[PDB]
Length: 145
Length: 154
Image (cartoon, rainbow over all chains, first blue to last red; front, side, top):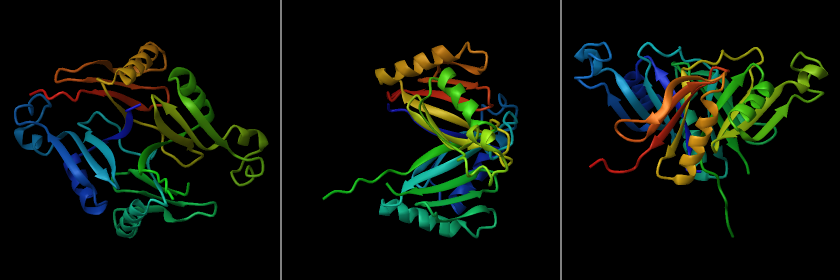
C-alpha cells in the first residue's frame, strides 16, 4: 500500500487555527487554499469574508500532516470522540528531541488543558494527553521497540 | 552494527461506547484486518467499577486496519464525547498505482449499498483530476476516500 490516513479537521476559522498551531504547536509547512474572490457568492459570502475563509488547508506538527477546512456551518463542533495520537520511537533520537522541545513549549501554555502530563510510564515508554483551545485532544505516545 | 528505528506517525484514536461490537462491525462491513483487542483483565475489573462479565466485554485498547491504514480505539467508559464529524478520516491513495486503486475501488463497491453507510458524496472522478468520495458509518465516523493524480495538468 501507498495509502495513508490523515485526520481532516473542520474549524470555525482555519486561518485563525493555522496561526495558532503555527505559534503554539510550532506547526510548519502550512498551505492554505482561501476561498477565491469570485467563488465568494457561491459559498454565500462577501468578497471580504471570502479572504478570511479556507477551502482546504494542511499543516505539519512534529513531522506529521494534519488536514483542515472551514466548517462553513455544515460540520459538528470539534470534540474528543476522535483524538489525534502521535506515536514515535523513543530510540529515534532526532524525533525524541523534537517531541521533548514541543512538550516543553506546550505544557504551561494558557490555551492547553493538560489531561495527563507527558511522562515515562511504569510499563515502558512515555505518554501524555492534552486538549487544545479548539477542542482537539492530542495524545503523545513514545514507544521502545 | 545496526539500529532499526521507527518513523513518527499520526493515528486517530476513536472512543467507542463499545469497541468490541465496533471492531466486529469494521471487520465485516469494512473488511478490516489485523484486529488486536486488549480487554479489561479479570482482576482489573475492580478498578473500572464492573464485574467479570462486563470486563470481558470491555476494551482498554484496540487497533484495526482498513485499506492498509491503522485506526486505534478504545471504550469511552464515562469519559469521551459522542463521535461526530468534527474530525473526519481521510484515506489518500495514488490513482496511478494499479494495485491500490483496485483495492480502494473494491472496498467502495462493497460498502455503498450497505444499510449502515450514509453516502454524502458518491465516490467519483473530480473535475480537476483524481477521485473523491465521503460517507458516514453507523458509529458516526465520517470517512473520505481521496485518490490523487500526480500528472502535471500543465
